[PDB]
Amino acid sequence: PPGPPGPPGPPGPTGPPGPPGPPGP
Amino acid sequence: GPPGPPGPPGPTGPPGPPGPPGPP
Amino acid sequence: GPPGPPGPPGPTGPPGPPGPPGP
Image (cartoon, rainbow over all chains, first blue to last red; front, side, top):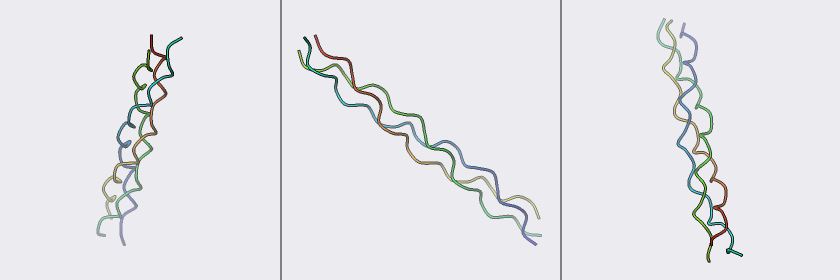
């Protein structure tokens, strides 16, 4: 019969940049 | 026997980097 | 039966945090 599932895949891609910050004081 | 199935997807990747500075 | 291969990549991470406030 089939062997067991493989292990987990790698961590996915890093997310995209954050939004720009707020207006300077 | 034949191979097992592929495994599950991995974990969610790290968060992205900080955005740029805001307006002046 | 030998193990299956590794899983596919996981999902893309969330957006980062906001930038700092400008000048």
